Image 1: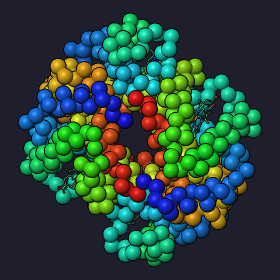
Image 2 (image 1 turned 180 degrees about the vertical axis):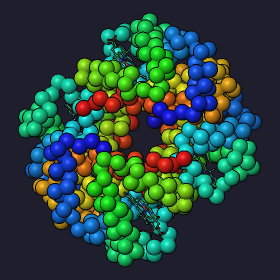
Image 3 (image 1 turned 90 degrees about the vertical axis):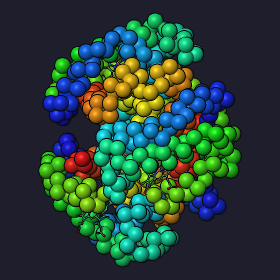
Image 4 (image 1 turned 45 degrees about the horizontal axis):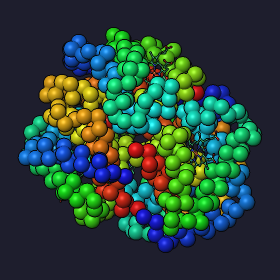
Amino acid sequence: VHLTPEEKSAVTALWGKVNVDEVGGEALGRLLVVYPWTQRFFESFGDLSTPDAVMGNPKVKAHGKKVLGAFSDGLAHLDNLKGTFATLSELHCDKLHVDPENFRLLGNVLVCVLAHHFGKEFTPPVQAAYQKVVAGVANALAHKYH
Amino acid sequence: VHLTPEEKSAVTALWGKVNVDEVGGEALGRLLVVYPWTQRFFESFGDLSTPDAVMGNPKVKAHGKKVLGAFSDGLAHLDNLKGTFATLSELHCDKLHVDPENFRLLGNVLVCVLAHHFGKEFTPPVQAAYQKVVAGVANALAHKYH
Amino acid sequence: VLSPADKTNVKAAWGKVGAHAGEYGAEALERMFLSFPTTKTYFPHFDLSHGSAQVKGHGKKVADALTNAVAHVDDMPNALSALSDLHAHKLRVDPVNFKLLSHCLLVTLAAHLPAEFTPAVHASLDKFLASVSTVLTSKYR
Amino acid sequence: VLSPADKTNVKAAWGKVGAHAGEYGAEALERMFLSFPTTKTYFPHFDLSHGSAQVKGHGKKVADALTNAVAHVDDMPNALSALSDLHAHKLRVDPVNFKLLSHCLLVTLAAHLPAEFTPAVHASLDKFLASVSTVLTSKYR
Ligand code: HEM
Ligand code: HEM
Ligand code: HEM
Ligand code: HEM
């Protein structure tokens, strides 16, 4: 999306400190706990009963790395998000049947996870920039839905 | 906004039979009756306590006529809604202080009014083409909001 | 938050629907699928084309459940308890899609009942559908 | 709806807030104005620069209103009665803006409560802020 040069440097600076596999499994974990109906796609994963079983589920961690890895590689192409995620958008629509609203819930959860891991370094201007990106990513992935 | 040859033809055809003065008066009135909190922007319009009073308000009728008239002028420029409504967008933001969500509520009420007036003529495909138009006009007006 | 006037407007308008409820149900669904393509993700096993009997059968089930609510407007939580559990623990439809269906349901009524769809009745129906949607998502978490 | 376990969690987390309630409420507003600029349309009569007395003063009232809600979680409609009348008949804020403020509150609590912001507490707080919003907008029509 349209981020000023300083906003992009802000986004890139903080992400370099992120453990992609850790945050990935933590963002998807809280997505399934806070918004339980998102579990409709993960019935084949196993025990999703309690918050503890979901956070400690290995299959939930496995997918979380896969999702956050695609997101991570996406930041290298912020000036062309629709072009980068054009294929994933088709797949999530015609084969996975994932309601795009799921992308907006995860983006918000990802922002809360970043506030938790970084604390006071996740200042208001920094949050402002990351919101535009979780929204830009969510829009690109929902672009090919028909 | 992007419309298929059949959609563009449907929207143009039906809009030729529309009496902008009467349809706009019906649309603004129903917005104030169904979603009463939108009445905050028109404290200087008079009696808005009851439904018959809102619909019979001459100031409500006159304003709906200007709004739909401006909407009408944008229909001739579906290829560049952002550039056409740029001035109005900046006005509703800097001087009017209108929350952009109101543009979306009006767009849906207008769809309910076109359905009421035309009956069977407003078929599902026609409505699908009109939801696309009102969503695009609402985004073009909420574009310069900083 | 449904006042006596609202309840009267609802019974009056839904009473005039009667036997055509099933046809109106299927039309509302058809309008939603075309106008809001995302909602199609919840019906990948259906033949979502015009005139589809599957959609007509579902439209009838939705319309009857609404007829059930209008008859128990003063006790909706218990009359839809079973449906609340089904959508919350099995179907798992994201809450935003209920507003999309409600709108399409209003558009259908307005296109079939012109004289009955006054700006006051319009107000009552919208509040009624929002209350139906609150009960259907009340047990999501 | 709020379960007994949810209530215990919200009271535990809010108990840790304590004195810093007013300061956090001010930061939650600043975060909202920057991320979602359309909310500024409800504050034209406020100086929205960093650390202005008006935003700090409003932040404290919003914090006090939340504290009373937690102290009366078993009966929020009677506790938030006057405030709901105020947002319904005068302020008339579109309901969509209540979600933007709740999100910004969660981000703030998450950035200041490293030990208490567990997944189970994150959930209960999101439900609690959903309930407060519903009660504040229950008299809109
Ligand atoms: C920012 C968002 C997301 C990104 C970048 C993303 C990325 C991916 C990727 C890389 C795959 C692998 C596809 C392949 O191997 O061909 C995938 C699979 C999938 N995604 Fe997403 N996704 C996102 C969000 C979501 C969300 C929120 C859900 C659901 C609540 C979801 C559910 C699925 C499912 C069920 C699969 C298949 C898993 C498997 O078969 O192993 N995705 N996604
Ligand atoms: C499709 C959407 C809309 C269009 C194209 C539109 C267009 C306009 C136009 C052309 C004017 C006249 C400006 C002037 O003479 O000073 C105007 C004024 C105004 N608009 Fe909009 N408008 C839209 C939506 C809305 C909505 C939904 C609301 C409010 C709920 C709104 C509230 C206002 C107000 C309050 C004024 C000033 C009235 C007065 O001075 O008494 N507009 N708008
Ligand atoms: C006004 C609100 C709604 C009502 C009254 C309603 C009613 C119902 C009823 C009566 C059933 C059938 C129960 C049975 O099998 O015995 C059902 C099933 C279903 N509903 Fe809803 N529903 C509502 C909204 C939604 C929305 C918004 C969606 C999705 C976009 C949805 C998706 C489904 C699905 C997937 C089924 C299963 C269809 C099948 O394969 O048999 N519902 N609903
Ligand atoms: C967590 C939800 C909310 C709570 C608890 C809340 C609480 C309050 C309280 C305590 C007041 C002070 C009233 C008095 O003077 O007695 C107030 C005023 C106000 N609220 Fe809310 N509010 C909430 C959400 C919203 C939202 C989302 C907005 C909109 C962007 C908003 C806009 C306002 C405005 C415009 C005022 C008047 C400010 C002034 O002139 O001083 N409120 N609210």
